[PDB]
Length: 279
Ligand SMILES: *[C@H]1O[C@H](CO)[C@@H](O[C@@H]2O[C@H](CO)[C@@H](O)[C@H](O)[C@H]2NC(C)=O)[C@H](O)[C@H]1NC(C)=O
Ligand SMILES: *[C@H]1O[C@H](CO)[C@@H](O)[C@H](O)[C@H]1NC(C)=O
Ligand SMILES: *[C@H]1O[C@H](CO)[C@@H](O)[C@H](O)[C@H]1NC(C)=O
Image 1: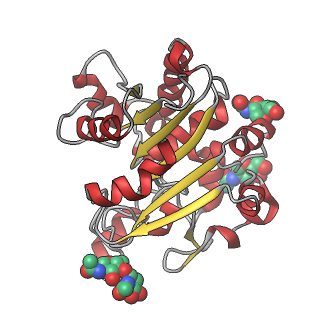
Image 2 (image 1 turned 90 degrees about the vertical axis):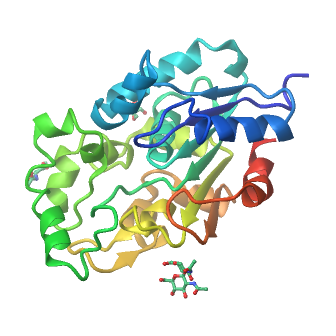
């Protein structure tokens, strides 16, 4: 029957598209090889690869989501449930879909290098040993939350300032929302717990995502930008505002980690660790 082959929904990262033979096109190919007959839907946000790639930089994420929710709803092969896999920012995005639109029901969710607590630093510009790097990021929180900037810059929508965190909570239009920052969204929690498995992949030697901990839902300790604490030690988990504590107890959260920089993995590893979560 069609059950066994649960469809897979893919969402590419920043700067990439749905159908590039080298990256997303190659993933879709591998999956199909090991799981004969599987329906794979690789999201394309926009009518052209042209606007797909740019919308990943310049299109309101809250809009991208409702739009994706609409696509999934008109695909008949997904009404009995589907699995989902997001690369880089696509991780948080698919997570947003899970909390915002429970129908069709997402089943397992694989986050490949996603930033679930956002970011606070620029790619390969560690603020520990550079006045410039540290300067810049700290001199952006001053604007990243302007309504005009938030509604036009995708990256700004998941920029998370640990220092002046009060402004991040009250002004971020995406991350703050799906992370229950303003107030606990009851459906959000119920919808996230409805997932069966939430796999979080983390690239140990990552130099693009600052902090790397964000890949496992961790982040810098409040008030500063030097040290970081894990998910288990954050209030989001302490008060279980999202249901991650209940999921963790029930074995719904899986944490994988490997060596390499951002989105750097081999076929071997993929076939070994990810394939099992799709079939
Ligand atoms: C590549 O980098 C990663 C992370 O930067 C290394 O993994 C661990 O990183 C932590 C923190 O830097 C160290 O305390 C551990 O000792 C590292 N693991 C081990 C076993 O050494 C990883 O080791 C680095 N290896 C490569 C590919 O250069
Ligand atoms: C954000 O909104 C809250 C609402 O309770 C308000 O108390 C707080 O002062 C605001 N934070 C800032 C500094 O924007
Ligand atoms: C989730 O929380 C409740 C539903 O139980 C509702 O007040 C809130 O608007 C929901 N969030 C959204 C916008 O889906």
